[PDB]
Amino acid sequence: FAWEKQQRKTFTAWCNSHLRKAGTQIENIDEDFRDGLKLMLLLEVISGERLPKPERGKMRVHKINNVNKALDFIASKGVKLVSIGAEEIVDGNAKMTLGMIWTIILRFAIQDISVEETSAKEGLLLWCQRKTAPYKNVNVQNFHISWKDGLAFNALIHRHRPELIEYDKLRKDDPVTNLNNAFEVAEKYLDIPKMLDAEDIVNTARPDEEAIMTYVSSFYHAFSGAL
Image (tube, rainbow, N blue to C red; front, side, top):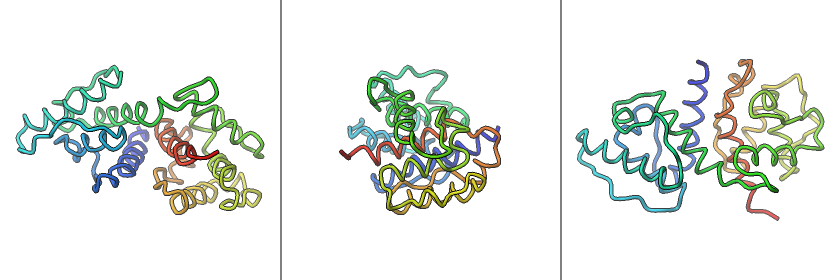
């Protein structure tokens, strides 16, 4: 669907926000993980742990072996992999590749989030509801339509860094302006790379929730070193 365009953009940007720390980047998410090398690198950055030595030989076995090293590692963190195999990743299955990157985001960015007595996706939601409670015209109830007008992004940033956001200036019926304001402020001041397209968000009835959770989780981690 339009899910796929959104996820390609967001998951690439998310991966790159981590790969920069390992001195590299991907450009094409359905080509650039096929040899398994940057996939293994990504896992090393986000876990802080070393994976086995990759094979650099460029034959299909090597790439399969590299991708299995990555999958075996994800599984060692208690992930039950579903409908993901190394051959299909190496062979460029785009939907499966997106699925595998989401699995990685969920485990390594989301799962360990702990807020009051809730964790993971539920904990990330409660955190957003707590931080945005007093803000006019914000009501976070999900990771889709709640985020679509741009105000919750701005409220979330304002609650931590009020000097960066003029919240009262923002118009609910001006969602593209609100979205770009938050995206730009986060990129410049919080070192959170842009992962969402304002137009896509506004021009979709229901924005992709995986893509929204991915971006919001990076806000959670930017703001977690405080207090």
